[PDB]
Amino acid sequence: CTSILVGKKASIDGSTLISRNDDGHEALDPQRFVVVNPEDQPRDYTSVISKVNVKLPDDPQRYTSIPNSILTNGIWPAAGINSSNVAMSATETITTNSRVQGLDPFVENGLGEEDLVTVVLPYVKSAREGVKRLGSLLEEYGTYEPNGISFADNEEVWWLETIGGHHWAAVRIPDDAYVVAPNRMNIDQFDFDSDDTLCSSDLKDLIDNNNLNPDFENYNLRHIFGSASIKDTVYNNPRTWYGQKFFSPDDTADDPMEQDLPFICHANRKISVEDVKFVLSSHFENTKYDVYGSGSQSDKTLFRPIGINRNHNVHILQIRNNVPTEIAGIHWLAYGANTFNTVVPFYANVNDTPVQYKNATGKFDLNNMYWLSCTTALLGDTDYDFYVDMRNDYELDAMSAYRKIQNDTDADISGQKDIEKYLENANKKLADVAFEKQNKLLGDMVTTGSNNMKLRYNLND
Image (cartoon, rainbow, N blue to C red; front, side):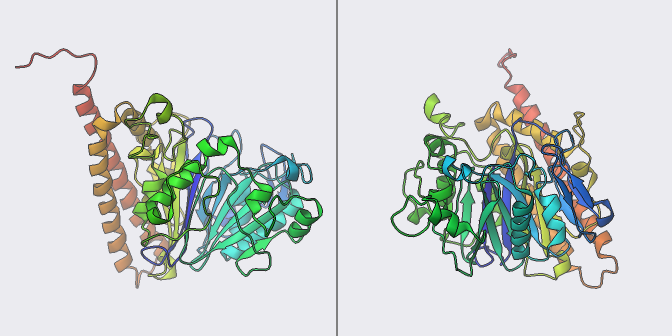
């Protein structure tokens, strides 16, 4: 997984953004776009993986989510926005170390990524409340994973990292800042009594009393609780580096393996949704580390890319400030490897979701956007340089169409007597166009690609 966070003064439009590539173990695993209405929410929750049993409040809020189609390993809702316009994405798998694990081991019947959005998001009305509730739950139930979780509302963006079986810390991202986060513990310099931090009440004592601090001065949480491994230099740090080079080129050096890249960054410009999607789809373009590029075989395969075959979904959760609250929450969504898809700006204030995004099952169905998008990216992968121009045209054409629909829908919001019905229609238009354009792209690739098959023999006349 790769996560990107953007504070409200750092975005081009004054919105907050939290985002993540939901990357799994297998390349393909069908995803659905689903609104969980309060009557559909469990009050007595039991996980599949850990069998943790969690009693939940009787007043859940409606929320969007991205559950797995195949429920063998549980729901895995990934991310969403609730009816209070709070966004949450869980999780970014991070790292730990043996010293803190020796003190606070994983809890095998605790909470995991399978569960987190389901047991937190419906019950909070601010990002800060999200942080606090998750912290309480970690203390009450424990966890069996090292995870990073993002929260946002129209004011604030928070990043929480879990530490051992029960501990945690969280940082409020400055308004004018952004973060790029890979599968490695991220929080660095940490001021315990700061207004911009929250953590386990015992976290400082845990550190001080057990000689966990490797530094001569101050507290750096990933120095203390995280990793700086050889594997980090190829699996994690280059992703951070590539993102920071894109947003902060003059503040970022030329070593992708760097272990102490800053957590909090300041870009040289305001950041768009298009920008975030670009970084979340990237593969070290214009470097020797690009698997589709000109580098040696060993250089081309050295680093884990951000766009990748096992992108199951990508979401950019946006809470806007230039609009009435009923259309503030936008759940941008796409499926499959990010090289050949586009995020679609679904309004989150709806009771149901469009069929092409809701209906994936374990049966291969090219009328569904999960299967259609995966098929497109796989074909694209077989000859990237051949297909990339059509890909590029499609991205501009599709995003332009989405924004036209969004702008038109936003402009006519006042006086709508049934908001949810109005926005479900807008989401239907968005999904219909997204499917038509995805399908036309694949068709164009198949048509031109068929001309270039190995199994050919043409008379040149």
